[PDB]
Length: 185
Ligand SMILES: NS(=O)(=O)c1ccccc1OC(F)F
View 1 (cartoon, rainbow, N blue to C red):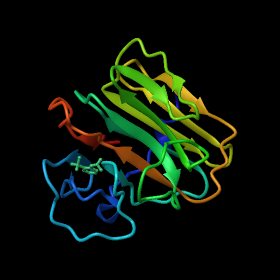
View 2: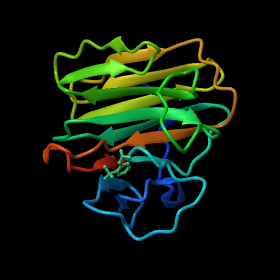
View 3: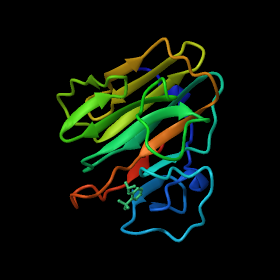
View 4: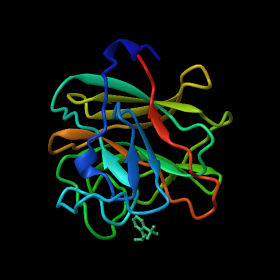
């Protein structure tokens, strides 16, 4: 792909984080802590899952960023509406305001309803995410495999400002402690 020139500097919004997450000083990395991180509760925090939003809001234009997923067993990545549900149980779907892909149990899937199997020959260590607001497109790229396309959501109905979306996943296995990291431009 040739989307690299739309690169944006994403930072994580601490106030939206699940209370077990640990965000680095530079707001560019996040991982699952082994306990509650001693923060007050608020209406923005994702309560049920290890999720956090980017601080940036997008309502027009083309945007691109990259995320490092090295040695993780489970994660979700993409964008979502600013007004997505924060509390309780929900599925990641465009109907609920999410445009995402994930790794889970050794398979990659797009967060359609129902979910779509992805075909990845080279397990990615870094993912590129491209949003074209006007066109209604969210695309995912395999940076480890020379930028090959993973998935395109088209005919998106954003219906609001978009925020970068992250889920570090649970660590029931002891094999999923590694962070998500926003990669430098
Ligand atoms: N398993 S846990 O108690 O450490 C936990 C941590 C963050 C969010 C949800 C959660 O548990 C359950 F709601 F899924």
